[PDB]
Length: 86
Ligand code: HEM
Ligand SMILES: [Mg+2]
Ligand SMILES: [Mg+2]
Image (cartoon, rainbow, N blue to C red; front, side, top):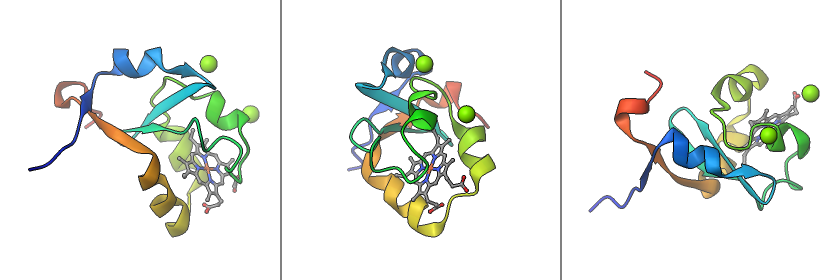
């Protein structure tokens, strides 16, 4: 009864512009198209990562507990395991 959708990195890479702004962080896939102007760190750092694995950039910032919880509402799925960063 889990209802997780699994994506490949090629599928994520198709969603690579500000109007379909997806990225991967720690093997979770997020669609932040509706978050761009709500992000305290601005929209450009997020548009720069559209279609990519943004894990290292996200971690370099050291986001807070509240930012980590806020992210969950933008999760749309997870990477297929064979492409995961382990
Ligand atoms: C593309 C990956 C991301 C990058 C590069 C990024 C970058 C940044 C930057 C530069 C700041 C300003 C704070 C600082 O520089 O000290 C920031 C703050 C913040 N970001 Fe992001 N961010 C990313 C993804 C997200 C996501 C998905 C969320 C959640 C919905 C989020 C939520 C926040 C919040 C709430 C803050 C305020 C500080 C904190 O709570 O940690 N960010 N971000
Ligand atoms: Mg910059
Ligand atoms: Mg780009």
